[PDB]
Image (spheres, rainbow over the protein chains, first blue to last red):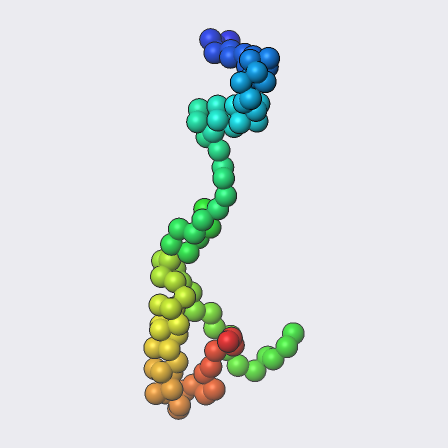
Length: 48
Length: 48
């Protein structure tokens, strides 16, 4: 069933006025709240 | 089908031991193999 969701609107004009890039906004929001797969490392011999 | 005389054995790291520990265990087996020349001949790594 449909559920409540949190709609956030980025204000493009204010961002441009402040000199903050939309990519930084979206990465910051998504990385923090959603998580982000950066790259791989080796845990006891296995790539993870 | 390449060489058909012989055996073709694979020694395996089953517990994330790593390269050095696996080489030591290889040497252990090759050294024990050399003590039985009545049963085993030319027991050697196929590697570098």
